[PDB]
Length: 43
Length: 52
Image 1 (cartoon, rainbow over the protein chains, first blue to last red):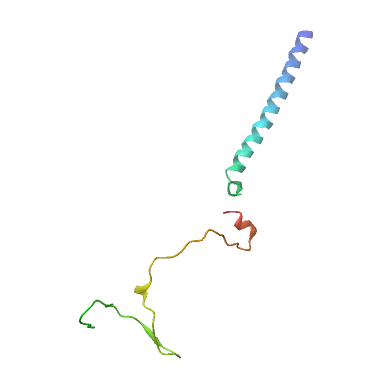
Image 2: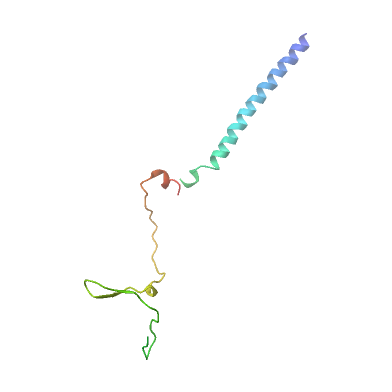
C-alpha cells in the first residue's frame, strides 16, 4: 500500500508539472501572437 | 498651328478669359522637381499616427 501511495504522489507531481508547463507555453504563444499583430515596432 | 523659326508647343491648350484677361495654364509645364521635408503631420487621430 505504501508503494501504491508513493506512486500516486509521483502522479500528482507530474500532473502539476504538466499544468505549469502548459500555462507557460500559452503565455509565450500569446506574447508571440500579440507581437506579430502589434504596433510596437513603430514606437 | 505654325511658328517658323523655333520650337514651340503643338498641342491644344484650354484657356480662360476671366476678370484679368487671357489665362493659359498648360499641363506640359508641370515637371517632377519637388523638395522633400523630414517633418511629419499629425492626423488628429492619435491611434492612426501610432500606426506609422
